[PDB]
Length: 17
Image 1 (tube, rainbow, N blue to C red):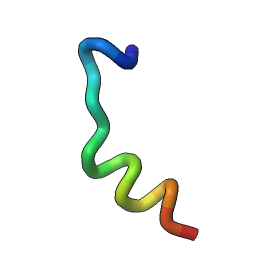
Image 2 (cartoon, rainbow, N blue to C red):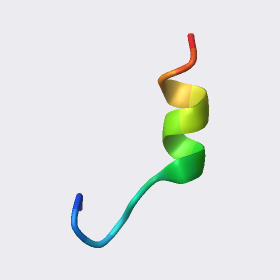
Image 3 (cartoon, rainbow, N blue to C red):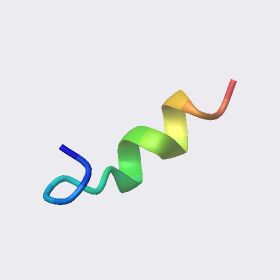
């Protein structure tokens, strides 16, 4: 979920093509 789980590491590699 958006409110509880942030996602620092997940966005740093998935959003980087």
